[PDB]
Length: 58
Length: 58
Length: 150
Length: 147
Image 1 (tube, rainbow over the protein chains, first blue to last red):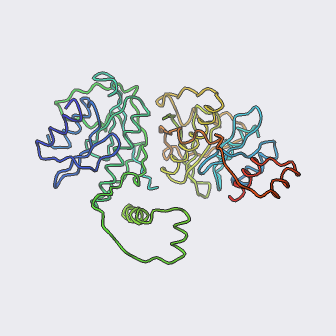
Image 2 (image 1 turned 90 degrees about the vertical axis):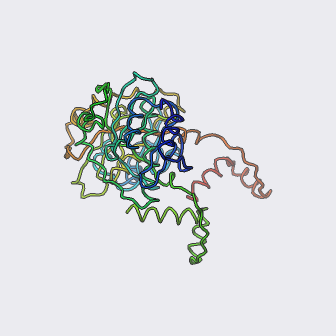
Image 3 (image 1 turned 180 degrees about the vertical axis):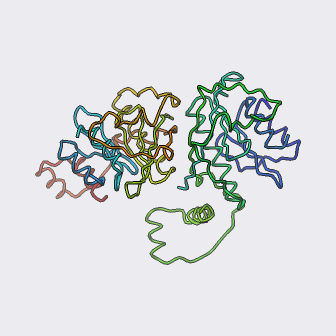
């Protein structure tokens, strides 16, 4: 997940769904029993990618 | 000038003219050759008052 | 408006993609992450992230965390990755800062799953509301969210 | 059009009080606004900033370069520190430094001329001119007067 699109694909494989709940430049991933993950548009650097991965328990 | 109104009054007496172009919760005072002064509505604490006075050279 | 403010950490690393300069993290939200190219964009993206996150807390009737005291925060001690050994951070701490981030949650509240509701309000409220050109539906929705927040 | 400046937020309880945060931008001399809580103080700081910067732009003055936030001190950057006649009482620990952002686009173009097509009776036309009125100014004042 150098990018938002790659992150979304990754999380989708792990059971997250992209909803319409996103706004502006962030999208919104939701999964039953988890607090949703909010993902920035475009390219994500090592900190952001890692933060989102840790949010997803991976 | 504990209040906006009293403050406007004070500056007006010292040659400032109240103006339109302050928006929202602030009003704008103007005078020739000076940076305009932006004044919050309602009661002003001693610091805000003092800063406004200092701007106007009072 | 419904304004909420949380302190955030702004970490400067312009290696690995300038435009990814300034990694943004809210200590009150575990592993929260967003980013922005300069200072302004970082704050804007932080606010946007915050708005979406808090709005979801409203809608799902979750708990809103209490904002941390900004003066007890540390770029070092509150580093979200400080402990996990896998990760090598390269932070420029001289360019990193701590700041408040505000957002109006009103703007981020979802309209999904619309429900039709018929009710009655007194004539004065109806005329007053219309004189201000209100959206009555949105006024009710906002008021409900606001009650939840407080 | 986003701009961001660091600001000092001074907590003072002694005012009795209402608005407990005095807000000051070091880059704008004697800049002053305030708010009751943290959120309001920031919002007012942002509004003050929008108006101030919009004025500088529309008057084509220069915008001050923003200070490095890490070089600021609630003590050393106190706007009144050199003023012999003033006494500050700050609670330093309840006071903080933070960035304040504003989109100046919302504050721009308020003096832009807007063309209006009006219909008035001839008696009003004749009367206004007999008084040498400025119709544009008279309408503007009338609108500002209704609130």
